[PDB]
Amino acid sequence: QVQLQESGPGLVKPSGTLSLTCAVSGGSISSSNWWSWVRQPPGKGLEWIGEIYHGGSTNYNPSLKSRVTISVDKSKNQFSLKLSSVTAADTAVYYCARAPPYCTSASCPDDYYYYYMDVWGKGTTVTVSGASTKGPSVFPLAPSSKSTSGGTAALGCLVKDYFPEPVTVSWNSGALTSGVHTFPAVLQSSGLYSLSSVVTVPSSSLGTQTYICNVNHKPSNTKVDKRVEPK
Amino acid sequence: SAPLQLGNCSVAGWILGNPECESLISKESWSYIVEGTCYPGYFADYEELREQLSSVSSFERFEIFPKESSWPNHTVTGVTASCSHNGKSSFYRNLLWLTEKNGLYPNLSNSYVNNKEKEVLVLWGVHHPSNIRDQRAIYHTENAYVSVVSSHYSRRFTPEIAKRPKVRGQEGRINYYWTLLEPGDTIIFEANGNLIAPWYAFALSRG
Amino acid sequence: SELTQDPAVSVALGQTVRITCQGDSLRGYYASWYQQKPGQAPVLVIYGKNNRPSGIPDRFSGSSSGNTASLTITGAQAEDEADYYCNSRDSSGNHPVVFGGGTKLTVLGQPKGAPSVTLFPPSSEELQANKATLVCLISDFYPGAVTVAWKADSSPVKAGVETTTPSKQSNNKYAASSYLSLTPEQWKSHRSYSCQVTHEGSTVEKTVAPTE
Ligand SMILES: *[C@@H]1O[C@H](CO)[C@@H](O)[C@H](O)[C@H]1NC(C)=O
């Protein structure tokens, strides 16, 4: 019933301030709920950041209290997160979630002593680096009759030279998920990322059907709809 | 004129629906009683209620407000360890612990008209949390009100918070109140929180 | 306090596994469990005393005994291979929330598969942009141990090679990608380029050429 939309920049300079915003739909921010924030560094586990009650009371992680500030804006039904003095340790994936109300005394029903986070945001990747944002160069990976293997052939798109993470690739604006496989990005020596998204498509259709990959790199607000034709 | 025997139960626990008094309520009439709060609190006009229940002639337990339909957009599944039964947490058989649903406790109202041609015994409770943090966690509102009004009864409850000594593993209290509804009379409940709503009532003659 | 759990555990398909999470913050409040698959967000699977959100099969069951909460998966399946985190709020002080270290669950009994290799030559648009890149895509191999070698006209090549770490596809098989960056004349001046993919001593090699 209640969903969470996340917003914010994907790149933050060192010593700067991280700023994210979570938007509440299907419910009022002024409800008995603890709006929380969670982050996850690359390759590590989940880390709780803090929570805020709609009255204004906050509760933060003791290890991050010096640099964390969580606010609430009842005018727009949103709650934000601000983290100052960022370093490479703050490069992580950040989530906004919802937690139920709870009690400190025994004068409550049993269901008010649970802790969980059932509604989550989709996740915003934040990178701490001094480099500059760069849009991607999308090149087609055309299907040739030498890379074919039976009644189906493989075609894809090459997303090259972008920064920072991430990049999402869909095919035919979502109307294609037959064999869609998007590979994790690779990090070049120049500091720019690159990944490929390939799809499995029948050998009979490659000559007559038009296939388009929809590359999205929101850190630069760039959307590239590239068409992949046979050679 | 056989007596009604409660066994190990008191009149308070029997009339409220204590989960430890489920095997009782065997008669429709009796001349005297032979004889208890699972969630601590005060029982107002208790010994006067025992006088009025000492001898009845047409006793009957009915559902005053069904578990569903009566209180929409409020949670009705509230149970506690103070009212344990078979190791499982439970609550009174005749009362509902109304709590917020989806983070909201909207202003609430419901009424019942006595069309059972006898006197109807309606009982309810008023919950007093022990800290203001849990008050807003359960009922959203900070200043709560509970309005009970009939043609011969009228009282508004403004529950406020205090830290009280530990009793039955609990430090908050629930005060229990009751009133008699004459035939044709109407009773209306209004609250924005802290209401232990009536779930089952009793119809009786004589007293 | 803090929550500690074993970093890894394995279970065969159709059997039962018990992921245990220990901490002094478990007696106070009730613990919750999350399932997280690679590249995705965590989803709540257990909260309270064995209460499942709508959409979680009854194979997932949670329990607690003292300072120990457990997540039990009955009749494990291949779709259950993910990370599992316990979560609870501490009962003292400002009541901070602590996450467990997570438990990587591996579901054993998956059939082994030879890698499937597809090598793409540089697109004409990239060449006309004065750049060349060879894309070697590997997929559907298990286990996820794969070493890649590139060849220019049968001579090994190490300059310009970038290979990703093996990642898990939706079918629980592993996949990886290899890139060799060239110049449009380094590409056109050779006879062929190859991508050697080794997987348990067995090598699959695909070859592209500018003339074709
Ligand atoms: C409930 O009633 C009180 C007084 O009658 C009123 O002030 C309050 O606004 C009502 N609740 C809501 C949600 O409006």
Image (cartoon, coloured by chain):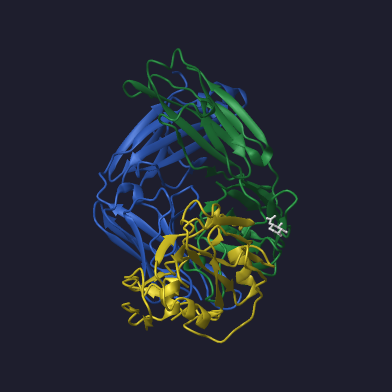
Chain colours: A green, B yellow, C blue
Residue A192 or residue A50, whichever sits in front: A50
Question: Is B70 left, or right, of B130 in this rendering?
Answer: left
Q: What is the residue that sits farthest to the right in this orientation?
A: A75
Could you say where residue C55 lies in the image, as x and y percent from the top left?
41, 48
Q: Inspect this view and state whether residue C193 appears.
A: no
Above-or-below relation of B24 to A181: below
Write the residue at 35% across / 79% down. B6
Residue B114 or residue A44, whichever sits in front: B114
Residue B141 or residue A120, whichever sits in front: B141
User: Which quadrant is the C terminus of chain C positioned in?
Assistant: top left
Could you say where residue A39 lies in the image, as x and y percent from the top left?
57, 58
Question: For residue C105, which quarter of the picture?
Answer: bottom left
Could you say where residue C12 lies in the image, as x and y percent from the top left?
25, 54
Question: For residue B53, which quarter of the picture?
Answer: bottom left
| Quadrant field for ligand 1 | bottom right
Could you say where residue B111 lies in the image, as x and y percent from the top left?
57, 56
Write the residue at 54% across / 64% down. B181
Q: For the image shown, how many numbered marks are present on the structure?
A: 0
Q: Inspect this view and state whether residue A24 appears.
A: yes
Q: What is the residue that sits farthest to the bottom in this orientation?
A: B165
Question: For residue A173, which quarter of the picture?
Answer: top right
Residue A137 or residue B56, whichever sits in front: B56
Question: Is A60 left, or right, of B11 in this rendering?
Answer: right
